Image 1 (tube, helix red, strand yellow):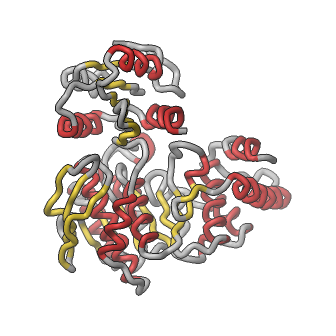
Image 2 (spheres, one colour; image 1 turned 120 degrees about the horizontal axis):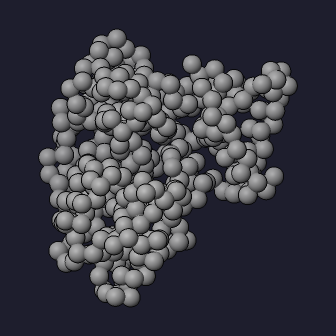
Length: 407
């Protein structure tokens, strides 16, 4: 297959649900998941950004780092990176061919054997990271924890950023139910770094670490961000933990939640470094954070005209954006919102000058309004060329804009 056919092959896999199928596949690929080192990252929100920064910091320190994240923003290849370089097209072709050949051998021994799409990609990623002999692979959990396709590893450190109800449809009706799923990535004697979890989620974690004997480092208990403020399109902040303070770090990320994610990232990188006796300096941490750009999440992509893209997709997500925009902009702005209810909107229209409401590009249109983001963008630029434009409401919308404007 060529590159186009290969990506198509990946997206063709079924939906079907222990880890027996993926473990069968990984066994045929020589159990790459049992070799090397891992950092395992979960949480309802912030797992991606934390994983990205952990990788940037460890890369600055001189490690070769695999990073497995979802979704992609510009191109599929981005889901599997080494030192923030997406898997090359030709390399993807050959890796797909290898895992395909393995799958096919298995289907000879057991006629109706198969795996899901996420199972296949995960297996491939574990195999590729081992082939290239990365020092460590930072692994973002797809959903939950315990039963996720990624959960076939013993990491050096586990991370639980936050527990909220966003994925309740799949993980349970209570915080306690969801927290139990996430706590499944906590392993015997392996340290766990968390956010300041809500009481029901903390109680689950407390009980888990009692059983595993894990060291638990908790945001706002064992580490914190005592100082933080806006500085350009980003934040200047101070990190504090058991060892003291790292002063006036800078990150090109806006949003209060990102302080927590970045503190979580710092504490994790430090834990990893300690557990593996690897040197990690304040300057390594400083350099890594400076590069910890996170595409399509409150990201300025053009100066003149001034264009910003964002993936906020829930009431609280929009509340957090509104307060951010208010801090970042004193002048009137255009907001282009495409969401998949009448809340999160209403809040927008009662906050900004021009609000346009559009469809999410890959979704059916369900029953001010424009037919496309492109039409809304063109209108604003024609009418008021110098008015900044923020496009929000959906990570998928934000990706489509980024592909068109930056590609």
